[PDB]
Image (cartoon, rainbow, N blue to C red; front, side, top):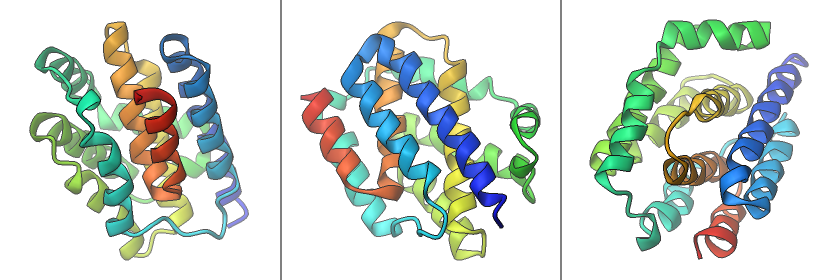
Length: 197
């Protein structure tokens, strides 16, 4: 495609928006990491997402960071925000943003992101979420589209968040880390250095 540039572009718009909403509580530095992330997405055509192993590496700099120990209430607010997602519904809304989100079995992709995010919050194991994306690329979905979909999904969840402010802060941080991991380890260092500490 050339219409891959389509999906990529409408997706960075969601990441940039995530950056505004969440920048309101975390600040300008966050607004900036999120927008730098959204430009990478924007111009990802022809690049390939980073390896399952490189990905867990950058992500672990974040999740394994003591300032990131999430409390149960927070963890319960974020899980519930996911359990309230209706994948068909969510697939349909992305469909309205653009034809290009109408990829083969998008409803199940969504549903897997949802379920493995829930697992991530509940057991602190981010492996299954990461392995889910990479496996779409291992199976033939263009890195562009995998990134695309993964990203829009997490961008839409974050935009719809209605949880307390500390909770939106912590979500926003892990959502930038999950996405950032597929792209450049730079993102992990910037969230770490500029925000978490």
